[PDB]
Image (cartoon, coloured by chain):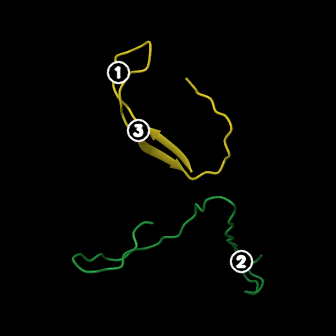
């Protein structure tokens, strides 16, 4: 099962991650079976 | 194939459905219909999983 959890929040900061707590809800549960090894982003 | 041919020689469309189970999660499921629900009475229930 390929779990993808997500969460959105506002922020006012550039140079580092914000300090604080917030939970990520589940969004996608892919019923696939591809043994993953690597990945890459697309911007 | 001709329309005047005998029914033994007329065209027939055949579809063979096979169900393959592998070492992977089972992703094709049946309808799995349901029934009515009753409250305030002792029942043996079977919800989603």
- In the picture as drawn, the residue positioned furthest to the left comes out as B40
Disc 1 on helix, strand or loop?
A: loop
Left or right: B21 as drawn, with respect to A42: right
- To which chain does the residue with label 2 belong? B
* Label pair 3/1, CB-CB below 8 angstroms: no
Judge the density around disc 2: few (<14), some (14-19), many (≥20) Cα neighbours within 10 Å: few
Q: Tell me, by letter, which chain the rendering colours green.
A: B
Closest to the observer, A18 or A14: A18
Closest to the observer, B39 or B17: B39
Residue under label 3 = A24
Which residue is depicted at the point 65% across and 58% down?
A: B24
Q: Nearer the viewer, mark 1 or mark 2?
A: 1
Q: Tell me, by letter, which chain the rendering colours yellow.
A: A
The spot of residue B40 in percent (x, y) is 21, 77
Image vertical order of residue B40 relative to residue A17, above or below: below
- To which chain does the residue with label 3 belong? A
- The Cα–Cα distance between marks 3 and 1, rounded to whole angstroms, is 16 Å
Are the residues flagged by discs 2 and 3 from a single subunit?
Answer: no
Residue under label 2 = B12
């Amino acid at each position: 099962y390929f779990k993808i959890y997500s969460k959105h929040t506002p922020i006012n900061l550039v140079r580092d991650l914000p300090q604080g707590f917030s939970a990520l809800e589940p969004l996608v549960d892919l019923p696939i079976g591809i043994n993953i090894t690597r990945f890459q982003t697309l911007l | 194939f001709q329309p005047t041919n005998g029914v033994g020689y007329q065209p027939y469309r055949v579809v063979v459905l096979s169900f393959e189970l592998l070492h992977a999660p089972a992703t094709v499921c049946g309808p799995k219909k349901s029934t009515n629900l009753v409250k305030n009475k002792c029942v043996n229930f079977n919800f989603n999983g």
